[PDB]
Image (tube, grey):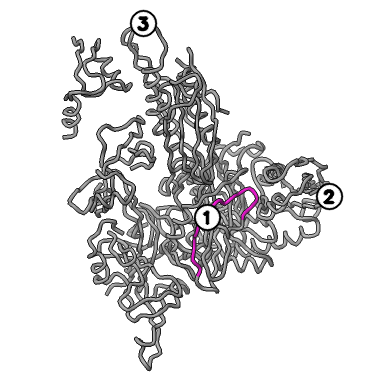
């Protein structure tokens, strides 16, 4: 988390797809050892396909420059998230910001 | 030779960790000498116990993940490296942490023995989320000084240990911050004397008068090479 | 049957025990039996893995096994997959909570038992016994044994008249109690019969 | 605004603190600048070049 | 670069410091007065040099 | 002939069969450094055996985090496959 | 074509050492020279080393 | 008073255990009685060493069970409980008995 | 050296 | 927890009023402790008459 940033850290850390930005908002079930499980609020939820969103976290693996790309959940269990919000911090990210 | 000798007159505990201590009376000019010498020794060479080997069940390496927890295993090893333990009799003990159920895993959940004292009952380690999840780690707490890291302790270890024991770096020194001040002493007949106000900040495990006594013995036994031989 | 067992004579001084527990006359025999069982099982399992010494140690109604092996990788397999498997079976054998530790044997050429096993294996796969013996001796010497002796006996080269042959190198004092004499034995179940292999490895003298 | 924010915290306005020396225990003359810079580790590591 | 800054700060002068215009019997006690804390590194002084 | 994936590594002694299983290949995890053996991979006729067994490069350490194997339909011993 | 296909993924953990390269965001390159102890660092009067 | 009966085959180990126990006692409570050595049981065994026959051929083994009697005169709140988490080294059967 | 040792002679073990 | 005691290896006596006490080896960051302590005592505390 850069103490002196410019505020463009948020847009770069979201728009580069290294963090697990929530597709549909709602609460959470948080099995998470394997995947973040998000229960969807009813307004964003389709009539059929009852549906809860299960995000795959990419754990310790090889990047193209032999660095380590790793995602860690930054939301707890039973915590509201909105559409477009971040859920898992990628490499060099801290709560959706950009921490090189 | 009209010199004097100092004593530890008042030892105030501001908290359980951050605690000042006076020294009185010091001679003229000696204040910064003893303060800087006790600072260097008290930051470099104090003995304190720390976590060395962590043994979690159903684990392969430290870069895996586990069932039912928040922090990953590297996060658990970092939060265990921050632990503050205070053993009394032995110099190498093995603790046990067993806990199931939804909720955070404090340091107060370790099934203590008699001679180990965990002085931080709000140190968080894990965040167990599944009620069917369990975690049973067996920590090993040695005792030394300085900084001995995992790379050097990769071949240094003689006692052939079995494979599966994660190696945590050893931050042995329990002193983190120390500042001294040379005030003006309130001596009823002398005005050219001073006091030394050492302001320690410990890990909670070390007793400040004991730390000052040990640093003084270290300095005296180092200077005996100058005293006796030439 | 001239000679005293080199391990057995030294248990009080320089050599330690394998089974390391206390029990009253009531539970002792049972414990022994359990130990025998578990050890037997382990031998059966970890034959391909080079295993030297199983050390059993049971405190507080819970069995702690310690397997000394040259290659932990084959005993452990994938990290905590094979060991874990072993553990439950051990527990079953005992009837108590089990705990397996695996000590890595540095220098398997200097471990006597391992050497013996190797020799036996060689014999089984139809090598010249003598050449095997030589190899055993030489290797140990190279590794830094103060001395080694090996002995093989019976139906050597499938010969009708059985005999014993033995190769010593360096010094192997057996009468000296303070000498660290790693002794052990094995048996090659060949087509012509059994061939017993003894091997003494003198690490050095302990001063206390 | 940097000076005013340094006045909200209890820090000196100039940005510069007097610093002592860990070796000699005695003050550096002419107070020095201490602050927090966001420093990065670039992937030119020395035990890939040796 | 660093060493010329150390020299330019060392051999310079200011119109008042600790030990202005005192007299010194050699360069050895000049360094002894600088180390003990009785003069300043730039304070004009009559010395006796050989 | 084809090359082979076996621990029965030659000339080299009780310094081959170590961070591996009885059927060959590094056994996962471990504190491997330089000069170790990861995948026993050597052929006969190549008293005429050799050591192509992919080892660890000089100067590096590490922990085997993952082993992938979509090998020539046969990699198995009698049964891990 | 390819027969025996075994890929092994090591993971070295490199710390920091005399010789690595660090840099800020402004173009201030640097090769980290000495890894000092905590004591020899310049501490301010509050006690914290830099 | 808490009487403690340490029993083991290895004497050194037993000694080590005893010391540890004392340490455990002494920090928490006060006036530990002391580590009193009782008589050692030397349970001997003779056996014929031949597989078939040779009766004068014999090995005479023994198991030396050592006893250490540690007593604690004042059981406090802190002290007695301290032993629960404080398990001793393996191969040493302890036997605490209050009163 | 003996000045400093006698100065620190008070609170040692 | 045992410390390294040194041996005083050399007194290179240049003149009757000169010395160079080569002294080895000490723990990491102890040479500065002993040297600075002795230097401040020898400068501003050693008794004598003039």
Name the residue: 47% across, 52% down: B82
Q: Residue A49, how many percent across, how many down?
A: 38, 91
Q: Residue at x 59, y 54 (%)?
A: C53
Relative height, residue C139 to residue D18 (above, below): below
Q: Which residue is mark 3?
A: J50
Which of label 3 and label 2 is nearer to you? 3
Q: Nearer the viewer, mark 1 or mark 3?
A: 3
Disc 1, SS: loop
**What residue appears at the point 80 percent right and 52 percent down from the top-left corner?**
H98
Callout 2 crowding tier (Cα within 10 Å): few <14, some 14–19, many ≥20:
few
For residue H55, the mark is 2
Q: Secondary structure at mark 2?
A: loop
Q: Quadrant of residue H31?
A: top right
Residue range (magenta): B112-128
Q: Is residue D31 one of those drawn in magenta?
A: no
Please, which chain is the residue tagged with disc 1 on? B
Q: Is residue E27 above or below residue C186?
A: above
Q: Dot 3: what SS?
A: loop
Q: Are marks 2 and 1 on the same chain?
A: no
Q: Is any part of residue F7 visible from this angle?
A: no
What is the spatial separation of the Cα atoms under label 3 and label 2, in whole angstroms? Answer: 99 Å
Q: Which numbered dot is residue B162? A: 1
Q: Is residue C53 left or right of residue E11?
A: right
Query: How dense is the environment of label 3, judged by Cα within 10 Å: few (below 14), some, or many (20 and up)?
Result: few
Residue J7 visible in the picture: yes
Is residue D19 found left or right of J8 in the rendered image? left
User: Is disc 2 in contact with disc 1, using a CB cutoff of under 8 Å?
Assistant: no
Please report, as a chain letter, where disc 2 is located.
H
């Amino acid at each position: 988390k850069p103490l002196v940033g410019t505020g463009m850290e948020r847009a770069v850390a979201v728009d580069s797809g290294v963090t697990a930005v929530a597709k549909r908002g709602g609460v959470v079930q948080y099995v998470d050892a394997s995947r973040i499980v998000i229960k969807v609020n009813e307004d964003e939820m389709y009539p059929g396909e009852a549906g809860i969103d299960i995000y795959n976290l990419t754990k310790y693996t090889r990047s193209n420059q032999n660095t380590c790309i790793n995602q860690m959940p930054c939301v707890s269990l039973g915590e509201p998230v909105e559409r477009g919000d971040v859920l898992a911090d990628g490499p060099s990210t801290d709560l959706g910001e950009l921490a090189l | 030779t009209e010199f004097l000798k100092p004593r530890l007159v008042d030892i105030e505990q501001v908290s359980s960790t951050h605690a000042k201590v006076t020294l009185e009376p010091l001679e003229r000019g000696f204040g910064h000498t003893l303060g800087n010498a006790l600072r260097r020794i008290l930051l470099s060479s104090m003995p304190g116990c720390a976590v060395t080997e962590v043994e979690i069940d159903g684990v392969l390496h430290e870069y895996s993940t586990k069932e039912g927890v928040q922090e990953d295993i590297l996060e658990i090893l970092l939060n265990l490296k921050g632990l503050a333990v205070r053993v009394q009799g032995k110099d190498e003990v093995i603790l046990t942490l067993n806990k199931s159920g939804i909720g955070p895993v404090t340091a107060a959940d370790i099934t203590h023995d008699g001679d180990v004292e965990i002085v931080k009952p709000q140190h968080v380690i894990c965040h167990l989320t599944d009620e069917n999840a369990s975690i049973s780690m067996r920590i090993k707490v040695q005792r030394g000084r300085g900084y001995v890291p995992a790379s050097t302790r990769i071949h240094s270890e003689e006692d052939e240990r079995p494979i599966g024991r994660l190696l945590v770096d050893a931050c042995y020194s329990p002193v983190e911050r120390i500042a001294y001040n040379v005030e003006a002493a309130r001596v009823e007949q002398r005005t050219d004397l001073d006091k030394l106000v050492i302001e320690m900040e410990t890990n909670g495990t070390i007793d400040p008068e004991e730390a000052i006594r040990r640093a003084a013995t270290i300095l005296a036994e180092q200077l005996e090479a100058f005293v006796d031989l030439r | 049957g001239q000679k005293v067992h080199p391990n057995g004579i030294r248990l009080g001084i320089v050599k330690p025990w394998n089974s390391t527990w206390f029990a009253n006359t009531k539970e002792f025999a049972d414990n022994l039996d359990s130990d025998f069982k578990v050890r037997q099982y382990l031998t059966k399992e970890l034959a391909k893995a080079s295993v030297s010494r199983i050390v059993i140690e049971r405190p507080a109604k819970s069995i702690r096994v310690t397997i000394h092996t040259a290659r932990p990788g084959i005993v452990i397999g994938k990290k905590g997959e094979d060991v874990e498997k072993l553990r439950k079976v051990v527990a079953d054998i005992a009837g108590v909570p089990a705990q397996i530790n695996i000590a890595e044997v540095r220098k398997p050429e200097l471990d006597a038992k391992l050497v013996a096993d190797s020799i036996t294996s060689q014999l089984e796969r139809r090598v010249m016994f003598r050449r095997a013996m030589k190899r055993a001796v030489q290797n140990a010497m190279r590794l830094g044994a103060k001395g080694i002796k090996v002995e093989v006996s019976g139906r050597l080269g499938g010969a009708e008249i059985a005999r014993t042959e033995w190769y010593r190198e360096g010094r192997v004092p057996l009468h000296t109690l303070r000498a660290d004499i790693d002794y052990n034995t094995s048996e090659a179940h060949t087509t012509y019969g059994v061939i017993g292999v003894k091997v003494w490895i003198f690490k050095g003298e302990i001063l206390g | 605004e940097i000076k005013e924010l340094l006045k909200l915290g209890d820090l000196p306005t100039s940005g510069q603190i007097r610093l002592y020396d860990g070796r000699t225990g005695e003050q550096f003359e002419r107070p020095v600048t201490v602050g927090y810079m966001y420093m990065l580790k670039l992937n030119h590591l020395v035990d890939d070049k040796m | 670069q660093d060493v010329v800054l150390g020299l330019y700060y060392m051999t310079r002068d200011c119109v008042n410091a600790k030990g202005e215009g005192m007299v010194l019997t050699g360069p050895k006690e000049a360094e002894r007065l600088y180390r003990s804390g009785l003069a300043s590194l730039h304070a004009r002084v009559k010395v006796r040099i050989t | 002939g084809p090359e082979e994936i076996t621990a029965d590594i030659p000339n080299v002694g009780e310094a081959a069969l170590s961070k591996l299983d009885e059927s060959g290949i590094v056994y996962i995890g471990a504190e491997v450094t330089g000069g170790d053996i990861l995948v026993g991979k050597v052929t006969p006729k190549g008293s005429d055996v050799k050591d192509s067994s992919l080892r660890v490069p000089n100067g590096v350490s590490g922990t085997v985090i993952d082993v992938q194997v979509f090998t020539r339909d046969g990699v198995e011993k009698d049964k891990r496959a | 074509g390819v027969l025996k296909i075994v890929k092994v993924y090591l993971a070295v953990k490199r710390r920091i050492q005399p010789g690595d390269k660090m840099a800020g965001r402004h173009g201030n390159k640097g090769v980290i020279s000495k890894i000092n102890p905590i004591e020899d660092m310049p501490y301010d009067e509050n006690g914290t080393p830099v | 008073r808490i009487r403690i009966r340490l029993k083991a085959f290895d004497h050194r180990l037993i000694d080590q255990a005893t010391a540890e126990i004392v340490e455990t006692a002494k920090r928490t409570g006060a006036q530990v009685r002391g580590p009193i050595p009782l008589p050692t049981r030397k349970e001997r065994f003779t056996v014929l060493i031949s597989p078939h026959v040779n009766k004068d051929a014999r090995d005479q083994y023994e198991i030396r069970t050592h006893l250490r009697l540690v007593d604690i005169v004042e059981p406090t709140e802190k002290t007695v409980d301290a032993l629960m988490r404080l398990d001793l080294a393996a191969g040493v059967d302890v036997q605490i008995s209050l009163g």
